Image (cartoon, coloured by chain):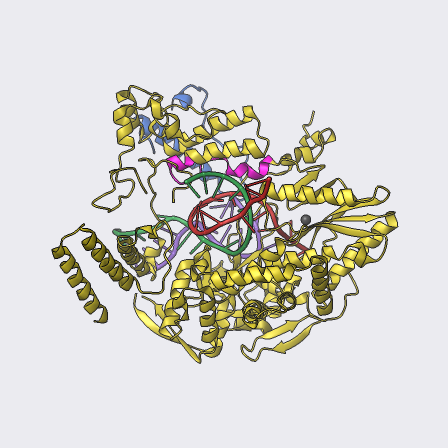
Chain colours: A blue, B yellow, C red, D green, E purple
Amino acid sequence: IKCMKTFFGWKEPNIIKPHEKGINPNYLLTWKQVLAELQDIENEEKIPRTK
Amino acid sequence: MDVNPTLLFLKVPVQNAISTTFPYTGDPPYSHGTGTGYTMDTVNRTHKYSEKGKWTTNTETGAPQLNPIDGPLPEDNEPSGYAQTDCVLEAMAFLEESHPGIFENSCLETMEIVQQTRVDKLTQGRQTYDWTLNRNQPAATALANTIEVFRSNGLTANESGRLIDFLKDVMDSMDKEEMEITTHFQIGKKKQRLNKRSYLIRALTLNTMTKDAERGKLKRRAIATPGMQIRGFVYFVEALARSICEKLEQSGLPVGGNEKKAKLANVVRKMMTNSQDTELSFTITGDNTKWNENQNPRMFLAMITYITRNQPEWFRNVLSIAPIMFSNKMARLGKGYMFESKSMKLRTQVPAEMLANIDLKYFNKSTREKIEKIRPLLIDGTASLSPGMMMGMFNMLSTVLGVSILNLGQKKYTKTTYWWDGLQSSDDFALIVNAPNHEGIQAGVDRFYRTCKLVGINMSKKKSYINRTGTFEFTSFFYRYGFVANFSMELPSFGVSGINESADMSVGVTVIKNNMINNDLGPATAQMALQLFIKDYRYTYRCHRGDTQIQTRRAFELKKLWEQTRSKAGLLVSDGGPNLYNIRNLHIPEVCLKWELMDEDYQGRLCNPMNPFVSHKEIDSVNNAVVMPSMEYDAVATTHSWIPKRNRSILNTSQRGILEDEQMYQKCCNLFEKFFPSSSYRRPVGISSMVEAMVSRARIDARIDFESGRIKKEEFAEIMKICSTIEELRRQ
RNA sequence: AUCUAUAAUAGUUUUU
RNA sequence: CCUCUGAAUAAACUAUU
RNA sequence: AGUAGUAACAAGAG
Ligand SMILES: [Mg+2]
């Protein structure tokens, strides 16, 4: 979390090079979920060992 | 500037940097699924190498058998198994001629070994194909089950405790019309009756599987596991072969390590000195293609028959049984295959017992061809494999055969201006050929090649090469005017063994020391290896230094211990202490190294005999003298000599009841140690039952104590009464 | 000067 | 839904005990 | 999909 905060310039994620055999929207949603849950754990006034 | 590591060889000779050619820092290849394909390929290839032989049907098992002995002489360079019996006999005869009395003395020593060996020798090993369960079991478990079945079938010569009596039991069981065994299911006990042919097929069967974690091979291969009936005969035959090999200079077995390197260097230098100063000398680094698939058990029978001439008949029979059993051997196919349906998205397991009459629409082209070729050989769920030695068996007898061919290279036998000698180890060889000119070298190489062809030995042309004497390779040792060091080969040994904290520390330091002594590991690299090992140890066992802030579940206790301790250097690394090891003290145990730095309370807690992490004895009440547990790499037992858990898979099978049995066995064994203290130290030998021996020992001890005044007459009377009660219980 | 005692554990070597 | 389980070839040699 | 490679995993059983 500390290292993520040190960077400014986040944009809205978009697919630049798609995976031919995959489902790219799933990757995009995975990234969004990671961001959301990072914020969530940051909002619970305690960081656990595992999430 | 593109970096090309290989170009380093333009200045450093390849041998002097050979360790760079071993990529032994990555994980080795593994086998994932079934081994049936490899077993079928091996069987088909073994029969293809002998296709021009004689086909017969075994009258006892009914299995087709192929006999390439005395077959047509080859007309090309393809591998072939048409060994000539007269040539093998002549090779043995000339080997005897060159070393008079070798076979006689070997047979004398082997007769002593055979007459002395005990049955418990069979408990050695890792696994064994148990014919009563059609799968692999621990060697001791397999032996126990076989003894139990034999006792249930009235075959009790093994009670003598001699291995040869167990072999007599095996032979007598071969003649039983029927056999009866017990089977478990969902954990009831049921009885199964095997007719003569079924039991005979089971007795000649070797299980097969795929080998995992082998370096330097792109493709996988099959390995075999012998059954219970054949282990003893193979053991005796290999004892004879070992005795023979110990008396030959060209033999690369059964010596190893520094002694092997010294022997090879001495032999090579003697060959060089014997070479004249006006004749060319060449060395061939050679490999033999499919050694074990071309050697035939019948030729080993012939060799044993020639070796054991003028010997008692019983010795000859007990030695000859092994090749007889191996020429009528069967091969288990394996797990089978797995089928997948994409439309229905399902998977299933197809056992190998169904391959006999399974429709071939499921399989691909290669597997279909394998099954079609191998079907004629299938009987009772196995495959008939008469020719060939399966895998890694009779290594020393093969060494004897190779050394005989090497011995055929003396001038008294070549009868010309060229000659040869060299080193043999199972199937690997180095050949030194001396001749006045190059044409002589060519003639000698050709004669060696053809003589090997006569005895069923094929020299791998694409893996063998020849150069001037002075450099070669033998059994992964690279000789360049002397054997060179190869550190990468032993590199995987560096790390954490996984026994426990104390043993792992000892193993790491000892490995560093030994590689300094042997593999030319330098001082600075030794220090860096020590640092890396301590880092890995701390990370694995969560025992970082107490004055750090590494978050682990064990950090709180270590921090408390660190704070309460006055002498920090006395703490072990397992207790968060510092590292006191350097080059000069790699040979000293850690606890002994810092004994004179430990606090009295910490030292007493560490070496407290009443620590539940190590068991306790029962003499008097408990031997409260030293921490006592099998103490390999653990000189002094402390609280860090704990024992980890056990795998619990069997709990979900029908064999879980066996757990109980072994536990009960331990119980009984424990009691036996209260009567015979030396049993743990040295293995007891006797024919009487455990209860009878214990009762006799109790009576004699009571008499001795009463006579010497150690006990009073009331105790003597009570002990005698209890002994009589035990005698009464014995009958009921 | 010679020097293969046993048993346990782990590691290494032994492909058409 | 719930219970349990996370997978031991042969020979020789090397090291420690 | 992916790991992977001559056969498997992508949980198994009760
Ligand atoms: Mg070779």
The rendered magenta stretch, by its main secondary structure, is classed as helix
The residue sitting at 53% across, 27% down in the picture is: B526
Residue placed farthest to the left in the image? B714
| Residue B600 x/y as whole percent | 27, 25
Instruction: Pick whichever, B646 or B120, lies toward us.
Output: B120
Residue B395, picture quadrant: bottom right
| Residue B389 x/y as whole percent | 60, 62
- Left or right, B367 with reference to B461: left
The residue sitting at 59% across, 62% down in the picture is: B107
Image vertical order of residue B188 relative to residue B221, above or below: below
Image vertical order of residue B665 relative to residue A22, above or below: below
| Residue B2 x/y as whole percent | 69, 27
| Quarter the C terminus of chain B occupies | bottom left
Instruction: Pick whichever, B318 or A10, lies toward us.
Output: B318
Residue B635, picture quadrant: top left
Residue B593, picture quadrant: top left
Q: Is residue B346 magenta?
A: no
Q: What stretch is highlighted in magenta?
A: B487-504
| Quarter the N terminus of chain B occupies | top right
Image vertical order of residue B539 relative to residue B185, above or below: above
The answer to whether residue A9 is visible is: yes
- Left or right, E3 with reference to B290: left
Instruction: Pick whichever, B665 or A24, lies toward us.
Output: B665
The answer to whether residue B395 is visible is: no
| Residue D10 x/y as whole percent | 52, 56
Q: How many marks?
A: 0
Instruction: Pick whichever, B273 or B154, lies toward us.
Output: B273
Q: Does the magenta stretch include residue B498?
A: yes
